[PDB]
Image (tube, rainbow, N blue to C red; front, side, top):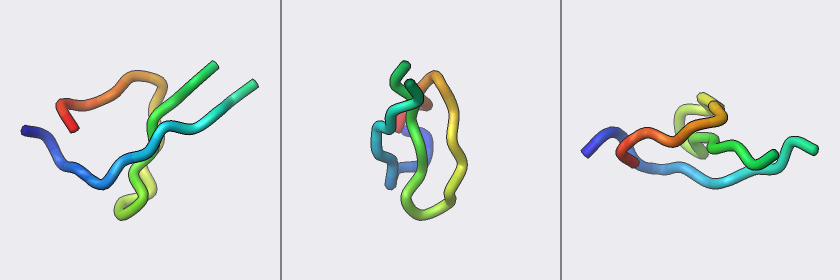
Length: 31
């Protein structure tokens, strides 16, 4: 499995962001 600790966020679109690592992207990892 790719690194955990993520949440879903809003940008007018939904995106995914890491609560521990702060990295933010429109498509999700294996996390």
